[PDB]
Length: 164
Image (cartoon, rainbow, N blue to C red; front, side, top):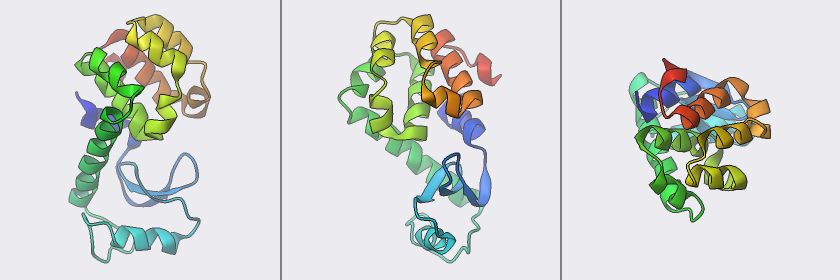
């Protein structure tokens, strides 16, 4: 396991336009196409992404999916490295826990995760179970419980147990 395999589990692989946890048009492996309510709007965006740049009509191959996936993951890592509150945290975690942090940014963006103040602090001080206890009481946790549980278990143990 690693970040890719982990996110593929959390996000699933959908070759056709779908709606996310929030009601937004996404495709593949969690690739948000557009916050607009229009499926046409969505198809448009899709047809225009450089990795695709063709006429899909809401349908992509398994390759294009992974290609967007790769980019999205990199984008996540960038957001982290470019965020002042996040970077310090990342630098301080091990290879497995780093995957947990990337998962949160991938899911919710750099800005959202940056606002997990108390939890980031506990993570920086290596207080696993407290970090865990603390994350479990967020709205993120109530919103996507299944996912959140595995991520938290990841921070807590520093093992892939929750995904195995």
